[PDB]
Image: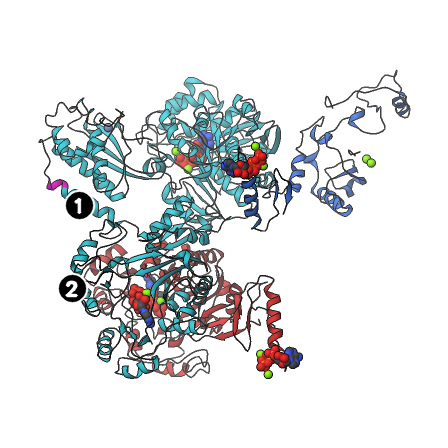
Chain colours: A green, B orange, C yellow, D purple, E cyan, F red, G blue
Amino acid sequence: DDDD
Amino acid sequence: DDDDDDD
Amino acid sequence: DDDD
Amino acid sequence: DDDD
Amino acid sequence: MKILKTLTLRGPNYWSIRRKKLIVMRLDLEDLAERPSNSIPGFYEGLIKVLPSLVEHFCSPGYQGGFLERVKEGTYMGHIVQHVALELQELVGMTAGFGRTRETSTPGVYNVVYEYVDEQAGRYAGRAAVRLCRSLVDTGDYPRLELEKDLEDLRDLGANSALGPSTETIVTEAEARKIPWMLLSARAMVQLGYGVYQQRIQATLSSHSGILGVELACDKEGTKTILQDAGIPVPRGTTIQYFDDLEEAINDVGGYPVVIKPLDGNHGRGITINVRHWQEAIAAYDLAAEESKAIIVERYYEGSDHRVLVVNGKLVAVAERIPAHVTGDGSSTISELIEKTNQDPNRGDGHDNILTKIVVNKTAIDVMERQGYNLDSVLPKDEVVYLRATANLSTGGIAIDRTDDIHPENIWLMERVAKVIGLDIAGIDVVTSDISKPLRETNGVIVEVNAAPGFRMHVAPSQGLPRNVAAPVLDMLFPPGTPSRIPILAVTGTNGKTTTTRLLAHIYRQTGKTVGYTSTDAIYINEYCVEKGDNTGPQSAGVILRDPTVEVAVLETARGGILRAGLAFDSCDVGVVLNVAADHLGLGDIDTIEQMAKVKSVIAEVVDPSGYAVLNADDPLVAAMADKVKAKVAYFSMNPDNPIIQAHVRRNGIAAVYESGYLSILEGSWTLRVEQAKLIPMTMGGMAPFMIANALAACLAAFVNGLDVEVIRQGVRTFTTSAEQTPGRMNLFNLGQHHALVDYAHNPAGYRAVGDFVKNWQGQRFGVVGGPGDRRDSDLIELGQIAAQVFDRIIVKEDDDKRGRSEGETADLIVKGILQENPGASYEVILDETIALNKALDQVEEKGLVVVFPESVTRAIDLIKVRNPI
Amino acid sequence: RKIPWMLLSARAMVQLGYGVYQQRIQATLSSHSGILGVELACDKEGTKTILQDAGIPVPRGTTIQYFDDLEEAINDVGGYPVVIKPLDGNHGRGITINVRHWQEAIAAYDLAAEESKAIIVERYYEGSDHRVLVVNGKLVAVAERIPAHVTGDGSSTISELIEKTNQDPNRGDGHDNILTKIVVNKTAIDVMERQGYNLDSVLPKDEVVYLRATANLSTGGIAIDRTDDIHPENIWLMERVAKVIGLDIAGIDVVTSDISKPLRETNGVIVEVNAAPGFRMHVAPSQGLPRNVAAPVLDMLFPPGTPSRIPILAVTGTNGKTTTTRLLAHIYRQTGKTVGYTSTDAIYIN
Amino acid sequence: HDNILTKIVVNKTAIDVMERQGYNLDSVLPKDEVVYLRATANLSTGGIAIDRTDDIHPENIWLMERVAKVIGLDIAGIDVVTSDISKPLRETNGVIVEVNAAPGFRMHVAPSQGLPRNVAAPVLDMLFPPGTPSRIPILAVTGTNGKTTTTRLLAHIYRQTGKTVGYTSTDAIYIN
Ligand SMILES: Nc1ncnc2c1ncn2[C@@H]1O[C@H](COP(=O)(O)OP(=O)(O)OP(=O)(O)O)[C@@H](O)[C@H]1O
Ligand SMILES: Nc1ncnc2c1ncn2[C@@H]1O[C@H](COP(=O)(O)OP(=O)(O)OP(=O)(O)O)[C@@H](O)[C@H]1O
Ligand SMILES: Nc1ncnc2c1ncn2[C@@H]1O[C@H](COP(=O)(O)OP(=O)(O)OP(=O)(O)O)[C@@H](O)[C@H]1O
Ligand SMILES: Nc1ncnc2c1ncn2[C@@H]1O[C@H](COP(=O)(O)OP(=O)(O)OP(=O)(O)O)[C@@H](O)[C@H]1O
Ligand SMILES: Nc1ncnc2c1ncn2[C@@H]1O[C@H](COP(=O)(O)OP(=O)(O)OP(=O)(O)O)[C@@H](O)[C@H]1O
Ligand SMILES: [Mg+2]
Ligand SMILES: [Mg+2]
Ligand SMILES: [Mg+2]
Ligand SMILES: [Mg+2]
Ligand SMILES: [Mg+2]
Ligand SMILES: [Mg+2]
Ligand SMILES: [Mg+2]
Ligand SMILES: [Mg+2]
Ligand SMILES: [Mg+2]
Ligand SMILES: [Mg+2]
Ligand SMILES: [Mg+2]
Ligand SMILES: [Mg+2]
Ligand SMILES: [Zn+2]
């Protein structure tokens, strides 16, 4: 992530 | 508008 | 005036 | 003047 | 032919958006309306011989011979006077070409519309066209002297209102840059820009010209003293207070080549330039002695007379001035040489051409005698003789542009002089033999600093290239990157303008800015009332636009103002059109709904291309205006599924819709909710659809002009028209699950005003308190029938305080009408609106609504309190 | 405030600050006073016209160019309680304040007629004469002006009352004390006669008699500070007047019965805008607290956070001054600034 | 990322979660009883996301902004546990569990209940604040002959204003  | 017309 |  |  | 009424339009209007300057004459063709040219023997030859220039008018036969080809084929007079008024103005140099005719009222009354340059000259030409035309249909000709005197009056009318050339120069550049301008009523001043960005000019003085610099520049000793203390070269000289001390002054100055000026000023008068002998010192003194009592006996310096123009501490232009003169152009005498050159095509009159005429007079002779010449003497080849002591274009001299020939050190010195004196715009008078060398090398001097200098010699030189002098002036007044205008939000439409205007002004005000607005109630700035009464129209808009404190202008715009005098502002940022309806048709020569739409569309068509038009998508005539608009279009509606809205947001437009109980903004695919209709106090609990529509229009206008949503929410929530704040307009009483709405009614529109809540009320019972007073004609039965078809709890009070109709007879007609259509609506009869019917609301069951139309609202809103309303 | 100052050689001007930060003053005019605002303020018709177009309350009146049209002007104005001023200005001269009768209209005319040829026959408004000082579009001070007068301080005559109060320790000479002396002259008598009194008459207890037509501290009147008693709407209106005319420092002459109520409630009017007003009445009032009038002036000329001085680098010593001075000026010059310097060879700028 | 929600999958972990609640896959639930099939909420595992943006109390708004500033993040996700987001956390005894750098946006731009939010707009507003440019001037020169000469002269003129000027030609690429 990158996208938590 | 646009001249002296009484068409 | 100067002082009006 | 006005226009000097 | 009689003229019944004349209107002068100044701004975008019904007839044209671009033709701002028009005169509309309402002409009554008592005769002639029945005589289309060929029924008037002589009305061709008389017309063409009196005004032969009419051959230049096209008319709709769009070719050079069109007028005068449609004059044989029969033409009615109300159309001819329009080609005569235009030509009478052209004959005196005022160019006008637009015009139109339409028949109105009863047969024979026409609206004659023509273009003007000067307002009084235009109205004059109209009246004159009627007289010329009437004489030619009575007799076959028009006296020459009755044409010549009219042309003389038009020439004078157009001269008296002219701006001087220095103001024309600034104004012309201001228009090129899109800076609005106005004449002010006092001291020939001109305002540039709107609101807080306004500037003023007066010829060559401006809002940035200080008084101390200007007064110092007019004080010759003060100027000389302050400049020599700064190390600036000035001429050497002294003072004599009209005593014969001449013999002494000359010795301190350094010898006889001296200059003697009058002690006080009187333009270019009483001045001797080069005294060479004692007896000349005496003659010079005697002339100086004519004026009031250190400008006496200056050293004479050799060189040419140069004028330097400095605008903001920076050099703009330089020109060399030379006195009227002739030269030895062959073996001719001076009077012969003068006639030869005074015929030059570039000379004549004044501000008509570049140069004026050379005039031989006793003063030309006095100047020639000092040079050893007179008018009958022959000059040696290439010898030059001056006919004037000083250089002035108005006396026949010349001006040569030398702007690019000035040395960098001299540029520095001239700018320093302007700063030492303290002038923004300054003319500097310099004497030097060579402007291309430093003044210290040529022994040049600075003779004078001139406040408010003219521009003619720099913008219209006789030799060299013209300079754009105005551009540096406008750049200091309106520096690059700054605005000259404030936002204008114009609101129009048949209904709801005042409500929309107050809400929109309220929302802007939450940003902390000074907001000015005009309405049919008053003119306001930040909640202070400036003027009261119906303040719509151009005269009020001008109060706000000229106000130095205003940052935002919100203006309700009515058809009265548009039809009577045009719009006051030319262009705006947001134009809102709320609706078009068949209300006030037949007035102002607008008979149909399609015509009324053209009156309202004026606002949409003046929105600047970078701005927005806000249109009502639920109104077929308003939505259609979108195809005329050059601006961006935003839409609002009460129906989210309106096909117009959907097509628009799918192309990433902006719209405001009422959906799911919310007022929201659609911005492409995203939805922004502002608030719930039920929580916005102006909306009657969510049961008055037109209040919702007005809130949507105000929210959308604020949004498209850049306000944030949070600001908009604050504004819609805190806005009021409270009972006993604005009593008399829709005062709603929420008494728990009991309701009453107090408003005023006379005719069906007033009853409808609360009939709308009744149709939308989410409850059990629908009642009413009377309706009409004694102000109505015998339509009481019909009003009673209407109430019967609307309400099931109808109580009669028609015995008012005014008693214009006896006592209870008004009620008796209401009773017949209400029983005729619905004889089962709790028809109690009280006949007392002061202590009983506006109190006895406990006769109506739960979730019952009672509609109240009292003769007096202020009183009814108080008596209803017996039931404990919010 | 540590701002340096110098007298200049011309027109009694004073320079404040150095180099590029300098400002100039001349009494109550400054480097920020525009010519157009000042000339407009001196034009009574221009001032009245521009203000009534802005929605500002001014007195109702007309013009007569020294013709006997007095009988007509009075009817447009609204009745006999009228004011007749000279057509041109000559300070406080040739003015009749409250014409009540036709023969007075004639006498007033004859005095107006002394000066050069619409300040004729104004409606007379009741109230006190207040002076409002506005400095940068913001209100600074308000004072109420009252004409020299005496009151019925016991059963004494007017000449006795004058001697009693003209001995007050706060009165005398001029700019020496707060108040000056009351002088009885033919003009005090003319003013007293119109009130039904003369110098040998006794006044009823607490009756007030004026010895002058107008209020001026230099003629023996008084000034009362009312700065904190002015209503917020009136504050807004006064600031708007200064901005409409275009003055930075302005005195506004207001007639009202109560400065604590809006002018529209008391039917007050604005009589005149004065460019370059004096400060004595605000800095040395006879009643109330003195105000620091200068502080708001210096704040516009030298706003907070800005300098009033330019850097000065002074070089001395027995040997090497000229060399050090030219090098130091050269180094500063490499920053692109205008550098001036003086030496034993010459004075230079860049 | 094909639809708003994904599929619910029964696995040994759904069973482990159900067993702790007193249920398993073949048991019947009482009317309106709720059984969770997962320990935590995640849209990618079959959960839901409800927009509550307009229901948050002003004090809680203040606290969340203060948390982001204390940690030092520009874009931050904050994980909060509370019984009622409309009351102050001190009244409901709520806590802040975690601050997440680089949070995703799916749940805010594509919620399963409530209205979608334009999350990107606030990001671009900090990167390119209102009133500022995102582009530099470009002057493109073409034609059959004279391009190189015109290009070098024009670059030279711009350079006299003191700016950094880059240019390309048939000879080379230059900067100042
Ligand atoms: N000491 C001098 N030596 C040589 N020429 C001079 C000298 N003083 C004045 N002049 C010239 O004589 C003329 C007189 O200009 P002046 O300063 O007296 O202003 P003015 O005549 O009163 O008003 P105006 O500019 O309209 O003519 C100018 O054309 C100037 O070039
Ligand atoms: N679309 C509408 N928006 C607002 N009011 C409406 C509308 N349609 C009908 N009405 C009714 O007519 C009245 C119009 O009042 P309003 O003052 O807001 O419009 P207006 O444009 O200012 O009228 P005017 O031309 O006299 O100024 C309202 O009281 C309302 O009862
Ligand atoms: N229409 C009026 N109604 C009532 N009082 C007035 C009216 N006009 C002028 N006054 C008063 O009369 C006096 C006259 O002041 P004015 O406007 O004529 O300036 P001035 O007398 O020429 O110069 P100065 O201010 O030095 O006395 C003022 O004190 C003013 O209060
Ligand atoms: N410390 C010193 N710095 C510079 N010059 C010096 C010094 N001591 C002796 N000299 C000599 O004396 C001369 C001083 O010249 P300089 O003009 O720079 O000083 P000064 O202060 O301007 O003299 P003055 O008082 O006349 O202006 C130089 O030519 C040098 O030869
Ligand atoms: N209009 C023109 N402008 C400049 N050069 C021209 C022109 N017409 C003909 N020429 C000639 O052709 C040559 C073109 O050189 P130049 O490099 O400036 O153009 P170019 O566009 O860069 O060629 P290329 O496509 O290879 O880059 C010049 O040396 C000149 O002698
Ligand atoms: Mg001159
Ligand atoms: Mg002059
Ligand atoms: Mg209307
Ligand atoms: Mg209205
Ligand atoms: Mg006064
Ligand atoms: Mg005065
Ligand atoms: Mg020494
Ligand atoms: Mg030295
Ligand atoms: Mg987490
Ligand atoms: Mg984590
Ligand atoms: Mg090629
Ligand atoms: Mg190339
Ligand atoms: Zn025609």
Mark 1 close to ligand 18, CB under 8 Å:
no
- The relative height of residue G40 versus residue F202 in the rendered view (above or below) is above
* Residue extending farthest left: E139
Q: Give whichever of F4, E822 is nearer the camera.
A: F4
Check the picture and name the quadrant holding the C terminus of chain E: top right
- Residue type at numbered disc 1: Glu
Q: Residues within 10 Å of mark 1 (few under 14, many from 20)?
A: few
Labels 2 and 1 in the same subunit: yes
Main SS class of the magenta portion in the image: loop
Magenta region, residue range? E136-147
Determine whether the beta carbon of the residue marked 2 sits less than 8 angstroms from the nearest atom of ligand 1: no
Figure check: E830 above or below E228: above
Contact between labelled residues 1 and 2, with CB atoms less than 8 Å apart: no
Reply yes or no: does residue E140 show up in magenta.
Answer: yes
Q: Assign the N terminus of chain E to one quadrant of the image.
A: top left
Are there few (<14), some (14-19), or many (20+) residues within 10 Å of tag 2?
Answer: some
Residue at screen point 48% across, 23% down = E791
Q: Which quarter holds ligand 11?
A: bottom left
Residue at the (15%, 36%) spot, across then down: E131
Magenta span includes E175: no
The reply to whether residue E186 is in sight is: no
Residue at mark 1: chain = E
Q: Which residue is mark 2?
A: E377
Distance from Cα at disc 2 to Cα at disc 1:
43 Å
> Which residue type carries mark 2?
Ser
> Can you tell which of label 2 and label 1 is closer to the viewer?
2
Q: Chain of mark 2?
A: E
**Could you tell me residue F59's position as x and y percent?**
33, 58
User: Of callouts 2 and 1, which one flags the residue occurring earlier in the amino acid sequence?
Assistant: 1
Disc 1 target residue: E152
The residue tagged with tag 2: helix, strand or loop?
loop
Q: Residue E317 location, x and y as percent?
A: 40, 56
